[PDB]
């Protein structure tokens, strides 16, 4: 009787679509199979977990890898439902919130609020809820495909999000919004398309955005660390956590490192909910090709590198922050 | 602008489903990724094409393999739409029919009609159309999953198909229906679960059903060879072709071989429309593990085997039909 290798509701919904729908979807899936994109993604997830969580045993690593594949794909289907739904419904999708106090307090302080959202869990579900208490200005990068871009921006417009370009005009508009006491959402854990700073990530110096830290340290806005995880029964639990006050100290690179620590701790606790498909660890000049070589050699290069970042740090010369 | 890496209608339909739908579908897809079923299927398609069409060049073989992956997946989504639709709509899905004359003539003869349908193209689309001219009795094997079985049988009941078990009681009911001048549909190109006859298939002796030939040679029913191919624009072209009269001669094994020839010719003409995922070539005691070993060694074993089936055939002893 081995089970739920389909549901009848599923089959009936697919069955009621036009033939064109099925043909287009099959062409999409087949394109994914024929170009090996699915295998490539699975292997990048596996390598990333080997890099960041080297203490897992082979068995634990298999369970986590399989669950992370499942969970990230699930998150993206969930995003489809979220971006097809009204604000009311998306708000009612939040069943439990932890740390709401810090959000309302940060809004009371009227110094601005920077919501720091890693690519983790079902993060797109939080926006509707946040939006009922504050205006939000958000960096937006148009999706490469026009129809998808279209869809996403109906979603964001329904949320009343103020979308701004991912360039210095968008950054200026975010500074302005924070000055007025409003809110922005930054996902800080991808590699910037242009620039910037070599900041350690799981012990590996990686080129990293400084945006969060620059906004926070200049405006003295409050920084909150946010994430949402699906519940056993169709709901989500949202978590709001204040950023360590160290984030205000030092250079933007120092604050960036504090954000990195928060991300690391979240992953350590919930490794199966991080979105591991992204090829983050390529962002070092020694690591440009680690997703394209033999996984074991890749790991040896990474280990060499983490080994040098320690002594060059006790050493007074800035080896690891030098960009060439 | 590279394109139709999604459509907006697609995204909006997925977006309007409940969150449960997305979670269940992602769990399904992820299960497929995590158990390597997708890679395994792709490799079985590739091996089957190497076995049956050894004259293809590597480039031609890649184009055909990719198109066959696309086309079989497309066929199954099309089956979903067909089995969710009314008879009227499914009939209007047939835009062009070739050889309709032979079908109406076979019904006029009132000796019964056996429709021989390879697993090819979009074969499930033909049933509704056939059903408006004749009653149909069909072998049915319950789908392993209960919900899917459910769905499929609403589809067949709406078609007024008389489903019968895949055992000798079903065979007796099909004989009875043919005696009355009615029609049956047999898909003859899979390996039987129990028995039977070593019949050459692309030069390889494979255990094969004899059902079609036994029905046809006893009842003298007319045998028609049927297949449907999707058109450029959302329709399908159906093809009805009389079976070579040799099918009436000799043993059931001889008639089975005539069906095999018809299938071979259809594949030679339309290799991209055959459903190549099925592991048909395992059905020989020398070939039990060819989908699980190195593809080149597999092909060497197959070539050895086709090499012996020739001389043992000119030789008077029945080497290849001996079942042990
Ligand atoms: C219909 C097929 C089934 C549906 C599921 C398809 C999964 C598609 C995921 C492909 C890989 C991720 O694809 C990537 O997703 C992110 C969101 O994370 C998009 O990001 C886009 O939306 C987010 C949030 O509104 C913005 O912050 C971002 O600026 C914008 O570019 C990227 O533009 C897209 O390239
Ligand atoms: C100029 C920096 C030099 C260092 C680069 C070295 C190698 C890079 C390692 C990982 C880089 C992956 O390269 C690319 O980065 C961009 C921009 O962040 C990603 O884009 C992604 O991040 C941005 C920022 O949150 C999101 O708006 C978007 O949803 C997402 O898809 C691309 O999906 C990825 O293909
Ligand atoms: C919701 C996910 C997306 C939908 C697409 C899913 C593709 C599923 C295909 C899996 C592999 C094929 O799965 C197989 O299909 C054939 C039809 O060809 C089914 O066959 C079933 O229906 C046919 C026609 O009504 C009958 O002749 C047969 O007796 C019956 O068992 C098998 O019971 C099933 O095991
Ligand atoms: C007892 C015969 C001894 C020879 C067997 C030697 C190895 C077999 C090689 C290929 C066998 C594959 O083994 C199995 O055959 C059965 C029955 O036909 C298939 O079942 C399939 O064929 C039947 C007959 O049309 C369809 O009703 C059904 O839709 C389809 O899924 C299974 O999908 C396949 O898993
Ligand atoms: C610790 C692993 C590196 C961080 C980057 C993960 C972000 C996932 C976003 C999904 C995607 O766009 O591919
Ligand atoms: C010439 C290749 C062998 C014939 C069997 C193909 C039938 C495909 C049915 C699809 C499936 O059930 O896996």
Image (cartoon, coloured by chain):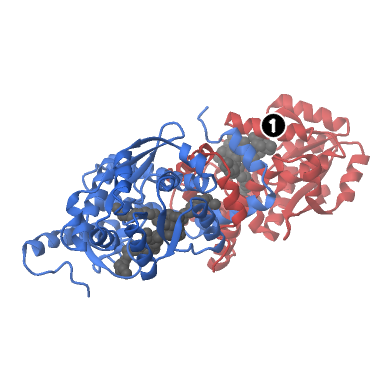
Chain colours: A blue, B red
Name the image quarter holding the N terminus of chain B: bottom right
What residue does disc 1 label? B153
Name the image quarter holding the C terminus of chain B: top right
Instruction: Work out whether residue B241 or residue B301 is closer to the camera in this orientation and state it.
Output: B241
Instruction: Work out whether residue B58 or residue A10 is closer to the camera in this orientation and state it.
Output: A10
A97 left or right of B197 in image = left
Residue visible at 29% across and 54% down in the picture: A111
Residue visible at 63% across and 42% down in the picture: A14
Q: Residue furthest top?
A: B169
Tell me the crowding category of disc 1: few under 14, some 14 to 19, or many 20 or more residues within 10 angstroms, Cα based: some
Q: Is mark 1 within 8 Å of ligand 3?
A: no
Secondary structure at numbered mark 1? helix
Question: Residue A299 is drawn in which quadrant?
Answer: bottom left
x and y, in percent, of residue A76 in the image: 46, 48
x and y, in percent, of residue B291 in the image: 49, 48
Relative to B213, say whether B269 is above or below.
below
Instruction: Work out whether residue A291 or residue A175 is closer to the camera in this orientation and state it.
Output: A175
Q: Residue furthest left?
A: A315
Question: Residue B18 is drawn in which quadrant?
Answer: top right
Residue visible at 70% across and 40% down in the picture: B83
x and y, in percent, of residue B231 in the image: 73, 58
Residue B266 seen anywhere in this rendered image of the structure: yes
Q: Quadrant of ligand 3?
A: top right
Q: Residue furthest bottom?
A: A324
B302 left or right of B210 in image = left
Residue B290 seen anywhere in this rendered image of the structure: no
């Amino acid at each position: 009787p081995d089970s739920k290798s389909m549901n009848y509701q599923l089959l009936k919904t697919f069955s009621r679509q036009p033939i064109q729908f099925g043909r287009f979807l099959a062409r999409l899936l087949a394109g994914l199979v024929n170009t090996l994109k699915i295998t490539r993604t699975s292997k990048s997830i596996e390598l990333n977990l080997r890099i960041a969580l080297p203490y897992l045993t082979p068995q634990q690593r298999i369970a986590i890898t399989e669950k992370a594949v499942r969970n990230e794909l699930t998150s993206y289907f969930e995003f489809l439902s979220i971006w097809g739904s009204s604000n009311s419904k998306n708000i009612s999708r939040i069943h439990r919130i932890e740390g709401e106090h810090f959000f309302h307090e940060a809004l009371a302080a009227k110094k601005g609020v920077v919501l720091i959202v890693p690519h983790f869990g079902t993060w797109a579900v939080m926006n509707a809820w946040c939006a009922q208490f504050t205006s939000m200005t958000i960096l937006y990068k148009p999706v490469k495909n026009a129809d998808a871009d279209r869809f996403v921006r109906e979603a964001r417009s329904r949320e009343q999000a103020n979308l701004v370009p991912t360039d210095e005009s968008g950054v200026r508009q975010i500074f302005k919004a924070l000055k007025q006491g409003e809110t922005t959402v930054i996902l800080p854990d991808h590699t910037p398309n242009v620039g910037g700073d070599m900041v350690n990530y799981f012990g590996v110096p990686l080129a990293s955005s400084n945006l969060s830290a620059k906004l926070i340290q200049k405006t003295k806005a409050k920084a909150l660390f946010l994430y949402a995880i699906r519940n056993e029964n169709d709901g989500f639990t949202m978590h709001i956590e204040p950023m360590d006050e160290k984030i205000y100290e030092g250079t933007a690179d120092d604050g960036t490192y504090v954000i990195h620590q928060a991300i690391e701790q979240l992953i350590y606790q919930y490794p199966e909910h991080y979105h591991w498909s992204y090829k983050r660890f390529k962002a070092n000049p020694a690591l440009d090709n680690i997703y394209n070589i033999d996984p074991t050699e890749a790991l040896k290069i990474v280990d060499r590198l983490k080994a040098e970042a320690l002594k060059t740090s006790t050493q007074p010369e800035p080896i690891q922050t030098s960009v060439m």
